[PDB]
Image 1 (cartoon, rainbow, N blue to C red):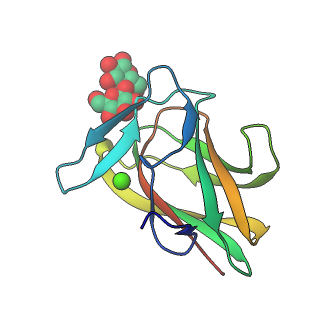
Image 2 (cartoon, rainbow, N blue to C red):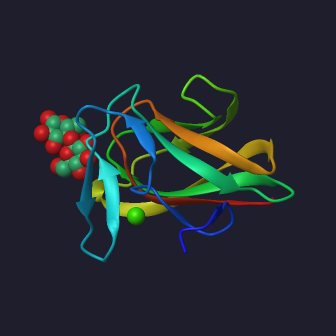
Amino acid sequence: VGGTRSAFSNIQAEDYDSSYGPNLQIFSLPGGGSAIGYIENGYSTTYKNIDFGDGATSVTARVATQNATTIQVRLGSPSGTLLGTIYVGSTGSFDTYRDVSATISNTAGVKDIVLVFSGPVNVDWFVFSKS
Ligand SMILES: OC[C@H]1O[C@@H](O[C@H]2[C@H](O)[C@@H](O)[C@H](O)O[C@@H]2CO)[C@H](O)[C@@H](O)[C@@H]1O
Ligand SMILES: [Ca+2]
């Protein structure tokens, strides 16, 4: 119960262990579950102890936004190694969620992962895979 979280099953974005974001909020979604939002440039959320097993090279995030932005995936801290960058084009509405993917450098073992935001976006969940 509450064991190590797999990188290969959805990680809920609201399930962060630490963050920088004075106005960042968790809120309920109409279709069930929750998202993080009220995000601004330089905000971040950190997810401890994610088990990448013997490696992942892709990330997918379920996101909503009205203006193009990016989400950096970093190792350990907001200033740690940049694993990859998710390019989030508009989904037309902060309430319309779509899946966007990106390549990451091969990440293996149990790792702390940080999402670093460049601008407004709502995030439901994210997950990793081997390309
Ligand atoms: O409308 C919900 C949506 O708001 C987003 O922030 C808006 C904010 O509502 C608006 O009052 C302000 O002027 O602009 C910001 C930035 O676009 C927020 O980022 C979303 O999380 C939220 O879903
Ligand atoms: Ca969620």
